Length: 104
Length: 103
Image 1 (cartoon, each protein chain N blue to C red):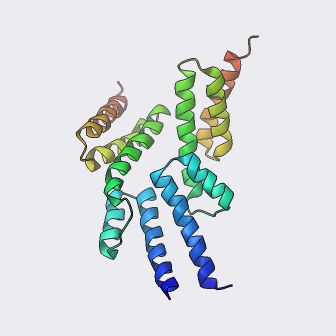
Image 2 (cartoon, chains in turn green, yellow):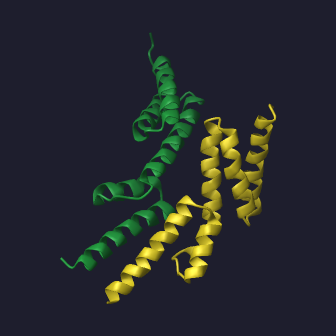
Image 3 (cartoon, rainbow over the protein chains, first blue to last red):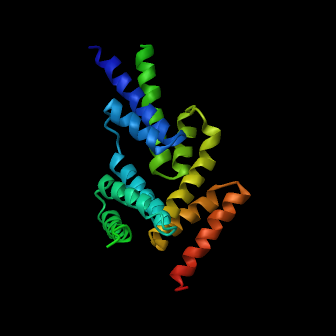
């Protein structure tokens, strides 16, 4: 259109996504990026950091015997990252949660 | 172009934010100072960075990566001007050192 005007709007959008990351929470950031369909430099690393956070939360749930919620966090962590360590730790805890919730 | 000026101001702000998120505070600080860039909410970003350092250090800590975590805690302890969050950073740093020392 005006190639200038378009690059400006995509810059503005990218800046808003980073502002949300910096000044609000991951959920706001992720929701903005998803519904605006943004390509964000370093998004993979940010996703891995969230996935490790999710493990951490899932662990404290696990260690307080909130096995049902813990499962949910580990599952989310597993599927958010492609980090092998994160996926391994998640999968390990997921199966422990499944054992705790089995009954059988 | 007010547009062309707008673009530049955004590109520089984008560079500053990427430094803030992905690099050290001092790199972000150096860039902003050198460019004379006004960042909205700048007065909050040093302490926010120290907090995010502890937060990420803690995620590593809780995944039993004490060696990795130490850097984050070290970085937060030296970055914050907040007595309390210095002590939280310090708490965690000492816990990491204990793990490195086999305790």
